Image (cartoon, rainbow over all chains, first blue to last red; front, side, top):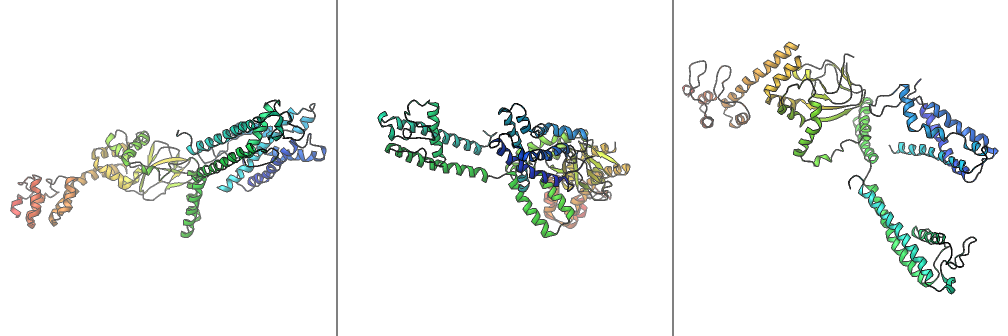
Length: 135
Length: 399
């Protein structure tokens, strides 16, 4: 099915994931510099923090485009997927894969740990929130 | 260059100047350390310098690439007015240079802030949009407008927020003569494709492009209602409309022309289906243009046919009656002796020599009422004197 992005539940979902955006944009520099492998004391937290950003990747395939040229709506399936797969699907999926598990179980290399800085991209969600307050 | 903003370019110029003076001041500062003998290197800013473990003892063979960064690190910290104290001047000749570099940069630093403010003070799309909504919300609250209307007025303001509009109160500085040519370049291709204006003269069509206005409508809005009196004529140039579903409106079409010609109330409701751009024409402006182009007016009615017979008969009757009506107006003015009233309908009206349905030259009424002054003017037009009505009389017989 298709859900219009106004029915008081998708907006509550986006506001819920904005909390994770604040957490994951402030914790990413804290584990790249200080920690060097993310010890097991917070192993569950790392896995749990990427679940909220993984369901949204498969839950953003049910939205309304509005087509940006004829402001009525878009409800077809091919249009939604082609829109998302062209804009930010590659960077959202890439910033969701576990890099701490890959880094340690790869003959630990510091080069492969620089991919954590990709996860800093999701601070743009907080910037988009401030734009809505201006309007 | 007009492609890029000039205020933003001025900001980049000041940053380059400030970062270049920092580079120059770093090279000069190291020179003031080498102008002392090597035996007195303990009195220099770098010779006596000692970081965490490094000593900077020799100071003259220190792998230049790590001798320039230390000097540049001093200059950047001073330029930004941060201040650490790990690197500082010690002798007399380095204090004097520091005073003139710090004082010079203080003026330059406050100059960057001044140009940064001027960039912001110009405004933005969000700032201008926010001001408009403040007035509209205040205007609607005091008049207690309905909630349905408030959803339309606020909708159109967000429509022009993105996809920047023509930016009104700016194009008004353009003279009307120049703007007249601008309208032809833009609106002509859309008008020529309508079925109503097929075969019309170029002179007639040109008189319509000058007095057109462009408007946008969001999907779901209603322009005309069933049974309403049409006061505007709309040309569809973009988007799609649905007439209520009994018909679908495509671009390069016109709707509402039936009501404005036969004086019939609008029979169908037009509904916006997608974002559309519409050109509108007023009723008063349309009829004034149509009256002058009498020959073109007949073609419009004929093209519309391809109630229809009644409209066609009325159109042929409308053009037949207007020639007789103007004759009556001139005779009435001459009967009451209003010289100024009849003057307007002579230079841009009808022929005074013509007679009405019964046959009444203005000389007949003038001679019957003894108005000497009006008689002089009719002589200037060389109006025939021996014109006879359907009675055998002459204008001289009334005097």
